[PDB]
Image: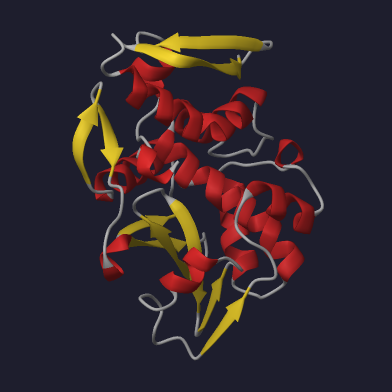
Length: 246
């Protein structure tokens, strides 16, 4: 399991937790030296448990699917909460089996659904380590509208930072003050499947992408990634979604 404590957290301990999260995810191959996540894992082994403590030391346990880093559900005291989607319902067979009650959240866990329930697009939600502290405190007290907002923060500060070194650095800069995500951060989040697929397809095509991936850069707009020598591939993306799941 991996754990992160917000009391005394600074950019370095957060960097250590994100390194541990990447290292807990299984892979057999590296494509262009990036870990390629497995196509499927059987049973309970498919789920990684993250223990997160807020500044006051209260905790939630989050279950992550190791083949795609998607958050399935979480445990707060004796209640488990799972997204309303089939994969999270399969995950409930393996994790948090000692929960006294199981609540299914009224939404699935993708960004479109969560932003509708929360009432705000995530360009307008501040993220950082203070925001993660607040997100953990909110999840301890069931409220489905408030939980959608907290889960948008939680997903971006754990799963998205594990997938892209740029987003981990964005959160390290927001260690003591939250700030809404840059447009670059939103584009990267949205492009992980696409980028993962084109890096895999570039093997056997001399490192050239079959279809270019367009991102928006940090200080402006539209840019096209066409091959694996790009900095997004060499220095940024840390994990690849297996094409068998795209």
